[PDB]
Length: 331
Ligand SMILES: O=C(O)CNC(=O)C(=O)O
Ligand SMILES: [Mg+2]
Ligand code: NI
Ligand SMILES: [Zn+2]
Image 1 (tube, rainbow, N blue to C red):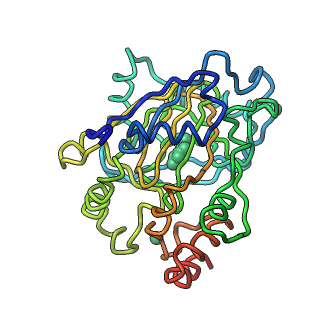
Image 2 (spheres, rainbow, N blue to C red):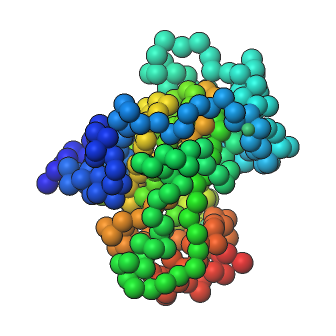
């Protein structure tokens, strides 16, 4: 078995290998990359997402989200308070202000220490989940707006034609902006490209050990656990690396820098934070190996998790028994 310790692997494809996306994901899995739950892909040196980022300040963040924490430093939840719209130029300026800017630090490890120590005492603002793309239409390789769709994958694998569409999302981050512990909708893959700015630190649990994280979470967030059998679908809970280590939960960490791709694999729980002002683009995708994960994916029926139009068909075809109760949660 390849990569039996479930280490995060880093790949350096050549320009020739960067042509066929599906084939390169399949190659990474042949080398056991999926066991970690997360892989890094450094693009060939000849590749570019677009010519420059000089012209992005007029993108609108219609609903910036202030991420307010409750709990203790290593075990907290966050809720998102809606703020007034602002442009990417206005957001960048806010991120760089004395109130919100990254503090002086030695290195990524020092900054990671400061994050886990101090996150709860601040409420950074996140421009998350903005439909759109920063890939130039002429970028032919690893263009996240031109991938094969999850609906066409399900159709190719299972023969059923379904409604729905699959498009990317932009995330504009600042120091301490945080993504809570989660897997993707229907335990899909995700791919994330860091277009510009400061780094993003990731934590990940190997898919084979996901249930260990869930059990810990039920112990640490006992009210939430009673409220919903899949409350991590709410995407609000954080647990620090120190707390994971104290409870024997297997995990790994890695920092993504501008120009790098990250791939999360089916049922790979992940969480993390941004180091300063940045812009990432991400999208869900599928492969034939996903289908079995989609059939077994947990679902939130309590009404909190509330997701996209396109998840309907996935639940309806892959999880017909669950569909009724889940749709009651959606309405
Ligand atoms: O970048 C973020 O805030 C969150 N991204 C992801 O969870 C992902 O790409 O799967
Ligand atoms: Mg603009
Ligand atoms: Ni994710
Ligand atoms: Zn729920």
